[PDB]
Image 1 (cartoon, each protein chain N blue to C red):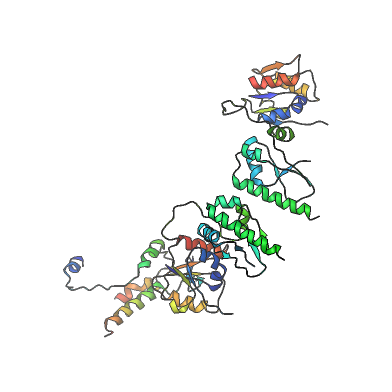
Image 2 (cartoon, rainbow over the protein chains, first blue to last red; image 1 turned 30 degrees about the vertical axis):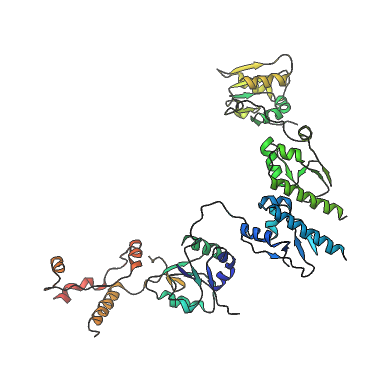
Length: 191
Length: 191
Length: 38
Length: 50
């Protein structure tokens, strides 16, 4: 299930495409926070799928201080809390021997600050979508099984459309009204 | 079960009529507090049926601070407490960077302050009362099945009484002593 | 009376096209030409 | 024709085969045929036949 689409559409929907795990092949035409210790970052990455960096005495930076509430929420062990507060004491001593720390302690604050949205409660299928690749290259026009069109234009889209319409058995979809991105996402969901 | 009554009686008993869910049709003749977050307001509205507004950085106002005791009493989750105290910290910072907050922590204080009385422990019927409408209009005199009279008077009540007494089969009730409102409420309960 | 639109590469169109009496002869002649292609 | 087709060895008659694609069946099931115009030469068939 391989689809061809205008380049601006994939450019605008790259985030959703990455979130739904379809690989992107496109041709162009012309401060973060860190966790005190690696264990908490690993736990939060496992829970939410969000990559988190680790503080390594680099520069005056902004530190995230996970609080007792989220410590209990994430199921963190006693040793993790102990090492977190040990690193906290080390930071206290370092800044007393003359960096900003935030004690985030609500789940919504952490979500609205950084990271990916939590997981929904449905059965997990083998794959999120039935499509593997959406591309905008003439080099793999024979690779495609269907294509999508929009009133928006690309300098190479006309030739690709001509070379794709020549296929004997290919599914063709066109969008005329509403939002192009919403229609494309609905199609990629139902295809 | 539709009733006709003098306008002053319904004017004086509008609160009870609204509380008992009978719709009012009448013709005339001539600072609040807010909750830190929407979740607590929604919970208290579900528990007591009292509409509560939400603080939105409007003006110097009066804030209700639900305390640990009522937090446990209302069955509030950990995240609700966390977000409440996060908003509290935000308010501390806002007023330190130069609004009144009250830490109500007894159930009776909250009841006597604002809101509706708690619920009684009886089986819940399909409907509170058997009557739907009490009105004071000649436009729906044929709508009524019974009417109530009192020594009190209205400029339109005499004509309505004459037009209602002409009905072949209509129940008539009159109050002579005691309190008019109490008699009317007892009648609307037993009818 | 016009046909429902059909996609021409990337643009919709509704032209009737060649007559059915003309299209048939072309197809038959093309099949025959394929017969004596060798 | 049909017994001849079953036998496989044609005699005194030869059909012609046209070739179509997979999606064509579905698209034909949805598209009808409306006879907008009649044949122009329909009025003069007997003369050319004779």
